[PDB]
């Protein structure tokens, strides 16, 4: 209902999303609070990606029943651009390749107003973001975000984009996949940096080990939130009950 | 101050060639007859220039050039075309390129046009590549109105040759873009890539016929075509693949029409509107971004 | 015992049609004139048959058929051709298919031939699809010698139509395979896939011309072509894409020549030799496995 | 030298592999012993994939200096098929898709002679291999190993293939990537099963958490084996010194 909504950034109420004849999300009740790293775990086919695309307003992910409230506003009639302008962003699992867009210009797209305006401060933010994702800024600034990059380079540049954007809500679809991750300390270093800045992360993942580093974890099984709360408790339940 | 061939209007302004790079030039029957000869062993790291300026009305800039590269030589040619007035212009280049054993030729042609489309840019290039030779070709027409672009290329490659041909175009108003390229991999292990990138707007007409023949064992090829359609533009993509050897392999991929939905939606998730996002994709596609 | 059309030699053996499925047939001027009419609302789950047997020398099995599907109807036609003698055979089918509003037609033709290549299988199919209609077509010729296959299809699609056309071939000896398919997406949101799979061995000659026209907003299409070349076989792949709307998008992908190196090497890492691994890939390609 | 070679399955001696003008492996000294899960860790560009392909004899991965001895035999003139017939196999990171090959027929390719030998046993091994990788045998046996499958389904079928094959040496390039792994208990269940059967696994990985479950770990940095030994020992070193 209306209980504790004043400290809630995102509120998904009994959401039903259909993909063709199949109902993928069968009543999703999920909330994201301010300054929280809330992870979403679940098996293949549970609706993890569908949920992330429905919140962002991606075409073809329209709810049949339910509502998505972001910042107190029901975003039912808002498009991707309008939802992004409210402080919500999505990092896809396989970030799109773009013909002829340099890294230095790509990282300026959607950049936070606190960096975006001053040029020498915006250019410094790019360096800090590329250095956080273990990429040499001078080796990548003039590279294109095209097919030429490795999947790990392109996904690290996408992680740097989330850093430059510094959103109120960052939806991260499988952030540790395809980056050639050395250890969870690499991704935790980025997660804690965004958290300290005031961001909330909606980390979508199938890897229980990644979810344990989050503040809260929700287990989605067949389009429904089965258990939610403590990361280690709901995590151990996920590994056991599948 | 550099081996360059300057042509203002239909006349040769300058013809200078350095040591190991013979540059000949004359005017006969209304055409310019150039001949570039790269001497055996000479690998020049600095690019040769070829400027073409046209400011007069009804100019027929016809240039027949022969480029010969001897065994183990190397050269890069940077052709620049400036046609800002564009009324009745006709730039026609007919080239015969012969790349010797283990020689390397690179060609880059950039065009800067004005906003009237009575220009005809018509390059015809015959390329013969010997064992171990390399041919790199790039035509870019993304500034002003193209007018009518009519490119024709035929490349015959022997053992261990490498070919890389590219076209970047930005067609507006009633622009016509015609591209017809054929690469014949006639020697063992000869490799090729034909790439086309571009955006077509308003009432433009694009025709891209790109062909690779894998006629020898271990010859490999790839055709990559991508063309954005905006407004009432019309595009035709004809990428032919011929294979006449069981150890040859050629692939082709093409995407024609509206911008990729994932690309558009990824930029809109950054706060850009559909028009800003499309503009970004199109600018990157044509090499502006 | 089922709505079927049997044709042994150049004569009609049987012509039986059930309730809601009118099957007419007659012999005129050396050709067979068939007419299939699926009545409005009739959605048949059991497939209609059409058997063609040829055991005599110099037979010209010419069949002109018209298939009409009324609004909300559904039918699947399974054509079976058995030509084991194959000395002077000629199977020619000229078809006019009209798929009504929200109707669904599926066609599957399978051929079983002997080791004589004096066979000419020549289907010409004109298909007209109304708002919401569906057309699924499959031609398989992987048994015995093809002889000369000459397929021609032209499909005109209106709003919300769905087209799926496929060809699986196995060409051996001096076999000739000719495929020419055009799909015109002339209505909003009309979707199409043209797929070609096959293997060409010995002295076979393959020509695959597959075309999609994205002429309306939200029309989408994809051409997928894959053809293995073994021996002295020759393949030509011509996949045309035309786009005449800024909200239309068509893609294509093709791989022609030797088997994919990663596929071959993955099977060889299982202990299979290069010939066993290639044989597995080719069998899977032609639908044997 | 010749010390302890009688209990060694694989012996890579000072191996130099060039990919174009670049030398990727600059003197690799690595050994794989009988009944051992020997993991290889390293950053991107270290030569992990190159090493796995050079041992298997993949075309384009020819050594310039050094030798690879497998089962006492120098396999310098042996092709992929000949090396596979000696008991060595490779599971690629992105297993190849195949047009028209069913799962039931794919899992019979290279299957161990202990199971291939009898139809009833071969059909039983295919069910336990698919059940081990958490796939419903009846839902996948008649599916094609083509583009139609998800990356997770195709890579789980590839792990099932390694099980059916039961090689003397199984080289596994990034076995936990692209499978939608619930936890390391899923991959460990498979690793222990192969180990109990007598297999040696040469697990190639960039993820330190995965290498901790192995018996021994070798750190490859810029084509050379820097540290080798205990999993937490060299694993912690890799996170710190990179």
Image: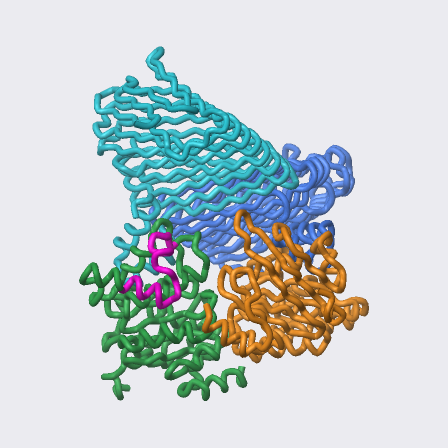
Chain colours: A orange, B blue, C cyan, D green
Q: Give the x, y percent position of residue C110.
A: 32, 34
Can residue B181 be seen in the rendering of this structure?
A: no
Q: Give the x, y percent position of residue B201.
A: 69, 41
Task: Examine the structure image and report whether residue C282 is included in the region drawn in magenta.
Answer: no
The residue sitting at 74% across, 44% down in the picture is B144
For the N terminus of chain A, give its image quadrant: bottom right
Residue A99: image quadrant is bottom right
Q: Give the x, y percent position of residue D160.
A: 34, 65
In the foreground, C213 or B138: C213
Residue D184: image quadrant is bottom left
The residue sitting at 70% across, 39% down in the picture is B231
Q: Is residue B145 left or right of residue A47?
A: right
Identify whether A87 is placed above or below B286.
below
Give the magenta range: D125-145
Identify whether A158 is placed above or below D205.
above
Q: Give the x, y percent position of residue A36.
A: 67, 74
In the foreground, D113 or D32: D113
In the image, farthest residue toward the right: A118
Can residue A59 be seen in the rendering of this structure?
A: yes
Task: Examine the structure image and report whether residue D127 is included in the region drawn in magenta.
Answer: yes
């Amino acid at each position: 209902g209306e209980f504790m909504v004043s400290i809630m950034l995102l509120k998904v109420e009994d959401l039903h999303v259909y993909r063709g004849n199949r109902e993928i999300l069968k009543g999703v009740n999920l909330t994201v609070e301010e300054n929280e790293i809330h992870a979403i775990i679940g098996p293949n086919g549970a609706g993890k990606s569908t949920l992330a695309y429905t919140i962002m307003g991606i075409s073809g992910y329209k709810p049949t029943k339910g509502r998505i409230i972001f910042k107190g506003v029901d975003i039912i009639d808002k498009n991707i651009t309008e939802r992004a302008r409210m402080g919500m962003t999505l990092a896809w699992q396989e970030p799109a390749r773009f013909e002829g867009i340099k890294v230095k210009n790509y990282l300026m797209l959607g950049m936070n107003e606190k960096y975006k305006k001053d040029k020498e401060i915006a250019e410094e933010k790019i360096r800090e973001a590329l250095k956080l994702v273990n990429l040499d800024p001078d080796k990548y600034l003039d590279r294109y975000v095209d097919e030429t990059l490795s999947g790990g380079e392109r996904k690290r540049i996408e992680l740097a984009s989330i850093i430059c954007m510094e959103p109120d809500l960052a939806i991260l679809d499988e952030p540790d996949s395809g980056i050639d991750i050395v250890s969870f300390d690499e991704i935790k270093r980025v997660f804690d940096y965004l958290k300290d800045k005031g961001c909330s992360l909606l980390v979508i993942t199938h890897r229980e080990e990644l979810a344990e580093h989050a503040d809260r974890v929700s287990l989605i099984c067949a389009g429904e939130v089965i258990k939610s709360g403590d990361p280690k408790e709901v995590g151990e339940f996920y590994k056991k009950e599948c | 101050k550099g081996p360059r061939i300057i042509v203002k209007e239909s006349r040769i302004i300058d013809v200078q060639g350095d040591e190991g790079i013979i540059l000949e030039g004359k005017e006969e029957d209304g055409k310019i007859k150039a001949k570039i000869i790269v001497k055996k062993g000479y690998k020049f790291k600095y690019p040769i220039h070829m400027c073409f300026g046209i400011t007069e009305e009804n100019i027929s800039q016809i240039i027949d050039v022969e480029i010969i590269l001897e065994e183990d030589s190397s050269i890069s040619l940077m052709s620049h075309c400036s046609f800002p007035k564009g009324k009745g212009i006709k730039h026609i280049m007919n080239g015969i390129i012969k790349i010797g054993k283990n020689a390397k030729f690179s060609y880059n042609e950039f065009h800067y046009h004005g906003m009237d489309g009575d220009i005809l840019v018509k390059p015809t290039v015959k390329v013969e590549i010997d064992e171990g030779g390399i041919y790199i070709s790039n035509f870019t027409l993304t500034k002003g109105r193209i007018g009518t672009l009519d490119i024709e290329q035929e490349i015959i490659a022997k053992k261990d040759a490498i070919i890389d041909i590219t076209t970047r175009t930005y067609a507006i108003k009633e622009d016509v873009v015609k591209v017809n390229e054929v690469v014949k991999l006639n020697g063992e292990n000869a490799k090729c890539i034909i790439k086309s990138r571009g955006a077509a707007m308003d009432n433009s007409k694009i025709s891209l016929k790109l062909k690779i023949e894998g006629n020898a064992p271990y010859s490999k090829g790839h055709i990559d075509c991508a063309e954005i359609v905006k407004g009432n533009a019309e595009v035709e993509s004809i990428p032919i693949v011929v294979v006449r050897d069981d150890k040859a392999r050629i692939t082709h991929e093409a995407a024609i029409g509206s911008v990729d939905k994932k690309q558009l939606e990824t930029l809109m998730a950054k706060g850009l509107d559909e028009d800003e996002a499309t503009e970004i994709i199109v600018k990157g596609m044509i090499g502006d971004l």
